[PDB]
Amino acid sequence: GLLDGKRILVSGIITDSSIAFHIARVAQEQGAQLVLTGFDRLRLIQRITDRLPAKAPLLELDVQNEEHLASLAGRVTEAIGAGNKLDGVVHSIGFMPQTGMGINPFFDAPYADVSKGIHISAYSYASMAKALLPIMNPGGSIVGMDFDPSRAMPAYNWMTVAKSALESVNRFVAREAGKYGVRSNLVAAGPIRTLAMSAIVGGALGEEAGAQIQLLEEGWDQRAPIGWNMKDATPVAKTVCALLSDWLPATTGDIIYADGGAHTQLL
Amino acid sequence: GLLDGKRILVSGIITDSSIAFHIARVAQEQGAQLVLTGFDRLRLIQRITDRLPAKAPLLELDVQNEEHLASLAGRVTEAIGAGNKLDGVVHSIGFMPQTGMGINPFFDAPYADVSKGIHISAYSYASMAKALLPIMNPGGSIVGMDFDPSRAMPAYNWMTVAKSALESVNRFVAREAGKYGVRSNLVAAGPIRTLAMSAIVGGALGEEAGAQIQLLEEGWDQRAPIGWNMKDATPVAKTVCALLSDWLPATTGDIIYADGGAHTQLL
Amino acid sequence: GLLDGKRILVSGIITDSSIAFHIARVAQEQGAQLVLTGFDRLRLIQRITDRLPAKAPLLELDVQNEEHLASLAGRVTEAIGAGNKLDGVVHSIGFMPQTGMGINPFFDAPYADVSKGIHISAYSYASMAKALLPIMNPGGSIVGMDFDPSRAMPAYNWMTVAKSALESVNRFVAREAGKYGVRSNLVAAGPIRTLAMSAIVGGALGEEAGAQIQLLEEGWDQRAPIGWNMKDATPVAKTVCALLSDWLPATTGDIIYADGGAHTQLL
Amino acid sequence: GLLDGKRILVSGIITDSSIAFHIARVAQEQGAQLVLTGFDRLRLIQRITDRLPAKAPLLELDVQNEEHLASLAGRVTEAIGAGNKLDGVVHSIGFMPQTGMGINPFFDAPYADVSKGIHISAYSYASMAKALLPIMNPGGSIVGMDFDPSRAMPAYNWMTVAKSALESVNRFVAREAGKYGVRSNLVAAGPIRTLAMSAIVGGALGEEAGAQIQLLEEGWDQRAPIGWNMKDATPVAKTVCALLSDWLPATTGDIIYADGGAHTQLL
Ligand SMILES: NC(=O)c1ccc[n+]([C@@H]2O[C@H](COP(=O)([O-])OP(=O)(O)OC[C@H]3O[C@@H](n4cnc5c(N)ncnc54)[C@H](O)[C@@H]3O)[C@@H](O)[C@H]2O)c1
Ligand SMILES: NC(=O)c1ccc[n+]([C@@H]2O[C@H](COP(=O)([O-])OP(=O)(O)OC[C@H]3O[C@@H](n4cnc5c(N)ncnc54)[C@H](O)[C@@H]3O)[C@@H](O)[C@H]2O)c1
Ligand SMILES: NC(=O)c1ccc[n+]([C@@H]2O[C@H](COP(=O)([O-])OP(=O)(O)OC[C@H]3O[C@@H](n4cnc5c(N)ncnc54)[C@H](O)[C@@H]3O)[C@@H](O)[C@H]2O)c1
Ligand SMILES: NC(=O)c1ccc[n+]([C@@H]2O[C@H](COP(=O)([O-])OP(=O)(O)OC[C@H]3O[C@@H](n4cnc5c(N)ncnc54)[C@H](O)[C@@H]3O)[C@@H](O)[C@H]2O)c1
Ligand SMILES: O=C(O)CCc1cccc(Cl)c1
Ligand SMILES: O=C(O)CCc1cccc(Cl)c1
Ligand SMILES: O=C(O)CCc1cccc(Cl)c1
Ligand SMILES: O=C(O)CCc1cccc(Cl)c1
């Protein structure tokens, strides 16, 4: 197993189409022992994760709650046993209020909404590293989920700005994590048909926002030299597991693109 | 004159070493008619700007104050006369609380502080564009000040994250501004010895933060193929005026580097 | 005039739709005194440049001819007068044999053909700098023409590789030019309907190569926040003149994008 | 084993400090069956590779020899058996004549020398893909070795330009390889003390070239958040094996940085 004997915390599961659900499944297939964290709807998340190949403890974590963050390391240690530390951490958490996405004009998002989205989607990558690095082993790995924000695009709007901030945060987290012998990297995935993303394509955020996202998805598979299947998160999950493994030991502060190669092609 | 007959709003003057003070001076030397905006210490700013080559109206603008922003376009129109519009806007505004910079550990900045810095330094670029685009002429130009955040560095810490967010915001502002025939760009300057920056090199934010910034300054002049004079903001001011002029008419959503070429060289 | 009193060498005119023809016209409109260089068909080029606003001396320069390059500085000095030096140099030269472009498979271009294209399109930027820097004034400016090669695309094929090499060459030319007080930069233009480019869209290099280039052109105007007019080279010419002027004095080794902002937008 | 059952061709071994020697060793440790290719000194290379964990067939390949390239696929098939195909290809080949590196001025490299270096170091990545893709399995992987050329630096000179060309070639090879279900990527390594590199630091290419490279090496370990050991190629070799494996299945046309994170940090 690629991750045999490793203890890995995975955040971000909310449905069976969550990218983090497939990260967790593949990590368990490869021998990892998991601790899961979930936000708000813990009964739902427990029912969802009962379908993973192995039972895993589930801890509550709202990344805006400083009490959850202050207690997290102790709750993880209780779950994996005293004297044991984590080898890996997966941040698969993102949110932007509806005013910051969709057909709602870019200029009309109030800063309170933008700040909440940047808190959950970017600052919390530093928050989780701060909480968990003291209980991580040398040779460990922190991985977060990214969507390439180097160019503007329709509808993503303020979430694009949040991802730009996240990429910057990751480079600073690498500086801190390096003192522990730990790597920090992001995986920039192509579009994946989660429940939330299917709802937006179906017009949850306005019709032409849905139309624009559908056009973006189609161009992605066209550009990608090996194609891109938005209905299959397994290639993204495998890439996260590659970064959690010992096989990219000299990569940190960096971004790995699991996007079919689409970002390397103009058309 | 490069800017003859143009009406340009310039924010960000607080002392005679402010980058915006030199932008304003060079723009007036080149024939522009200015409206100035200032934050908080308006009596001080009026005294400072009395030393500009020409008298200019000074308007109060705290970019965190929605009432200041809601009234700004009307106050500008009163200052330049009904039926007149702006040809240019300069955003030269930045702030990050001390916890987000210096020797203070990156992980110890509370989100309230980071969010305030991102509000002032990044979101407000969109806020000012929203306020002023309705009173801008086709062919107009919005310019903001940047510090290349593509790599992490010591001490800049959360201000680096704010600049990453600003670069992303600029690409979305270009989308909106294009509907008015207006360009939006950033100037990424090398280090400039403002009053605040001299204080930090002198240890206002901790000793080794000051030591690290001094090392960064020295490496900049070494890397720059044409050298870099941190005591001379005129090359930065001229670059801003180039973007305000009609001579870069097909550049938008972009970043122009006024840094001596340092970012193009590894050592 | 933006370039009043400046002496500027302009290469690359072959027809009245050459980008260099419009660079030369705008530079003369702005007060520059020009020396022109032309390749092979000098009688044709003289007839073309008789239509410029002012008469300019025309010198022969095949950038693959070491004798032309060894004599160039002396021939320029004869044209502008002893004791006078150049303030600006424009490289607007590119060529790739047909096997390296179009529907002809990427793998089927022989290296002899690729090497000729890289010689003319990339190495010659260093060759011209070597020849002309000894007769350039401090504060001078070298500008070359680029087409953004950071992503692969259909049909451009080996010319894309040549532009990647050119961008690298430019960063090294900046190191050398800096010792003379001279800047070196590229302008990355959007697509322009030169005679050669119209012929390729019309199928000179194969039908689906023409089809692919037409699709690339259409997406460019769609992406550009201020639009893109492939029939109008004046915005590109003005950007070159901006870099030749004194108004971007701290930019070197760099690339300025005169592309409507298209490269800053995904769709 | 990470590469259990995979058939992989590895080029570029010349001494026991070659990066390709360590790629080959790690690949064999992980269960791969290798075919090796060597240039010119085949008796030496056979003696060197006798020290690998397993015996591997050695084929002659001068990438400038079209007869070697035309026969390569048939010689590989003879070595692995009819009906068998390759799963992986490693390009670890580079050369630039001495005039294109070191204290020898950048402008003094003749194009004949530069063209030879670009032939061996960049064009040959396309040459090898053309030769070997017809005998590669779907799901296969082509990997080449890179040194980040996005910024100029002392001494690397024309080899930097060759690496810029290689990165561009890789994006086009990905387009071709995708039709076979094959990925193409580069690994950008930090500096490694090969025999050639130790000789240059010792002044083989001039004293201040050696001095400049030693300064570059020292800054690399300082910048890298996890450090950088130029005497240990194993982290680079493991990264190549990661790309040869099935664990980065959605990455192509891309560059993975095995450099300690140094390129993500300014200082
Ligand atoms: N789906 C795509 O197309 C795509 C592409 C690239 C990257 N990503 C990124 O992948 C990450 C996971 O998103 P997803 O697509 O799997 O959608 P998802 O809705 O399944 O996951 C989002 C997760 O964020 C969590 N979350 C929200 N607020 C939180 C809080 N205050 N505290 C803790 N957790 C909170 C949700 O509970 C949920 O588990 C996100 O960073 C997303 O931006 C998604
Ligand atoms: N000095 C450098 O080295 C350097 C280098 C590159 C970029 N920059 C950028 O240039 C910009 C101008 O900074 P400076 O170096 O001239 O320093 P400065 O201190 O002279 O200017 C900062 C300005 O921000 C304004 N400001 C702060 N909070 C505000 C608010 N709530 N509303 C409105 N205005 C507010 C200040 O009043 C002040 O005028 C900043 O964006 C800075 O990041 C500076
Ligand atoms: N047309 C576009 O869409 C576009 C876009 C971006 C950049 N560019 C670049 O602009 C430059 C000028 O090209 P153009 O579009 O105006 O086409 P063009 O055909 O009008 O100019 C090409 C020039 O290269 C010159 N040339 C070729 N071989 C030469 C040699 N051995 N010695 C000296 N000169 C030689 C030609 O004589 C000709 O004057 C080129 O670098 C081109 O790549 C063009
Ligand atoms: N050593 C470093 O610091 C470093 C860092 C990053 C990347 N790289 C790259 O790694 C690759 C391998 O280089 P290395 O450092 O292991 O040095 P090396 O000298 O051990 O390997 C170079 C290889 O190129 C081969 N070669 C040269 N000409 C050839 C030809 N005509 N045909 C076939 N093969 C030929 C040599 O025989 C030799 O095996 C190169 O692309 C190099 O640029 C090296
Ligand atoms: O980050 C997310 O959750 C969604 C990422 C995304 C995919 C496809 C289109 C867009 Cl606009 C955005
Ligand atoms: O944006 C600012 O006001 C300061 C920019 C800066 C210059 C030199 C060093 C650092 Cl760390 C930061
Ligand atoms: O460099 C040149 O002369 C042509 C640049 C170009 C424009 C539009 C499409 C393509 Cl593929 C290439
Ligand atoms: O590609 C190669 O073989 C050498 C790469 C390299 C390492 C360290 C310093 C320099 Cl200048 C170059």
Image: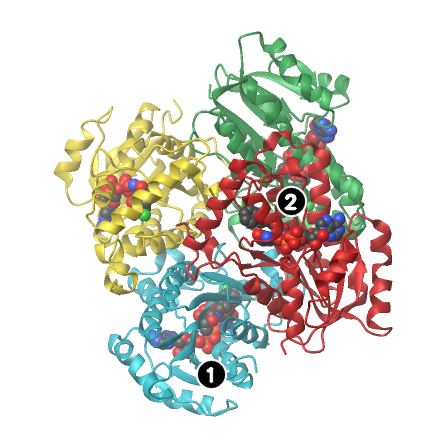
Chain colours: A cyan, B yellow, C green, D red
Task: From the viewer's perspective, tell me whether residue C116 is left or right of residue B39.
Answer: right
Could you say which is closer to the camera, residue A109 or residue C205? Answer: C205
Percent coordinates x, y for residue B214 in the rendering: 30, 43
- Residue drawn at point x = 14 percent, y = 32 percent: B47
Marks 1 & 2 on one chain: no
Q: Amino acid at mark 2?
A: Ala
Give the position of the N terminus of chain B as an image quadrant. top left
Percent coordinates x, y for residue A97 in the rendering: 36, 68
The chain identifier of the residue carrying mark 1 reads: A
Cβ atoms at labels 1 and 2 below 8 Å apart:
no
The chain identifier of the residue carrying mark 2 reads: D
**Residue under numbered circle 2:** D162
Percent coordinates x, y for residue C105 in the rendering: 79, 52
Could you say which is closer to the camera, residue A215 or residue D117? Answer: D117
Density class for disc 2 (Cα within 10 Å; few <14, some 14-19, many ≥20) is many
Q: Secondary structure beneath disc 1? A: loop
Against B114, residue C132 (above or below) is above
Q: Tell me where residue D109 sits by quadrant.
A: top right
Percent coordinates x, y for residue B237 in the rendering: 35, 32
